[PDB]
Image 1 (cartoon, rainbow over the protein chains, first blue to last red):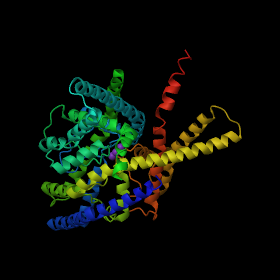
Image 2: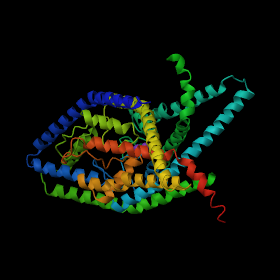
Image 3: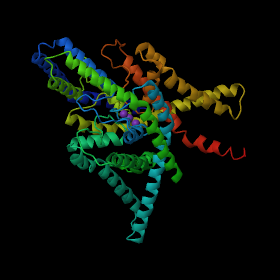
Image 4: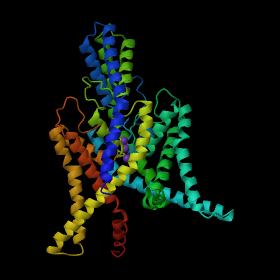
Length: 256
Length: 256
Ligand SMILES: [K+]
Ligand SMILES: [K+]
Ligand SMILES: [K+]
């Protein structure tokens, strides 16, 4: 499509405008609140002049630069054996959340090598896993529909059931799980589920990382298994690009 | 098959071990240094009590959640027109830097659907322009090599030249450009280059977002264009998956 790039440009433009009108006033009022609360904090202690608060902000911005927390009790220990097991998984999945990242040059270069040698490995593993699940699921579905009441287009209904299963278990139900275990309303839950599935990983919402919470010994592992199952399920429709694309576009000639 | 998953488990285990032994010591030193700097800020300021520092830290962490900068002069305006355009560009690329993200429930709910409708669109567009570039490069290389001496391996030489060209232009050379314009030592530039090429996007390093730096008027657009071309070259190799995979491993059967 020679007009596909024009579509891209128009889409980028309108999305930028909507994001502007939606978020910019919030950012302005947030900055204004930050400024007035800084001023109020200065009024709380005139003995601490503006420069003292500047130095405080500098120490804070450098602590946040070295990974440690800001609020207090920065004893989460993101870099121990059970947790680095999880950070390694979000690297080889191209999620790259952003709440934790290497800070040492040796560590940075090792992370480069680890990604370079693992991302292809992890992607092939996930592709094979998803292909195996898809094959076995189609086999069992066909065996049930043929031994039972046979259908003319059972394959269409089968893939419909499969896609609704995926969308239900990965974008609708997890918001309710995280509502009770992570204290997120449905909007944040859906937002985090989608950010994770697409391997976008903004990292502003990460499950199983909250110092003021109680988690089971194998909770983060359950979350990681959920993430990997999501990526595996997605791999099928990633591979069905042209097949499903023409399958759905064959009827578009009637609609347009 | 089932042995591959064992490879994955051992890979994750050793990666977690090395990542621990690398960052965990420096993370502990960072935490202790933050603690000691806190104690120094406390002792140097008598009127600033422990609870006062707690309140300041909480207010900073609260504003830092909204996206504002902690340092000062947060006049970057990540949500003006061009910055929103570039953010939209990163979102639909599965990069998700995660240094900026929508903080409004309406904004998050809109970003979910924006991703849903753009990520497949942008992936298709990148794949199309990549196949275009690859076909043009292939026909040009063949027209050049058929004039002079040719061979069956000639196409293999063309593939090798294209591989090394991509490696140089997107992985090895950019660190020098960013040493010039961003003042990153080579390891930082290489780390950032790889992270953005593999669509990990940790967001610790982003090219073109610095309040104190003085960038050109088209700097960010050029960076984004280079990113798009890099991901196009990446997709070209992605679609070259199994052509080289099964061709070479069978050649070693005759070697023994
Ligand atoms: K990604
Ligand atoms: K990311
Ligand atoms: K990502």
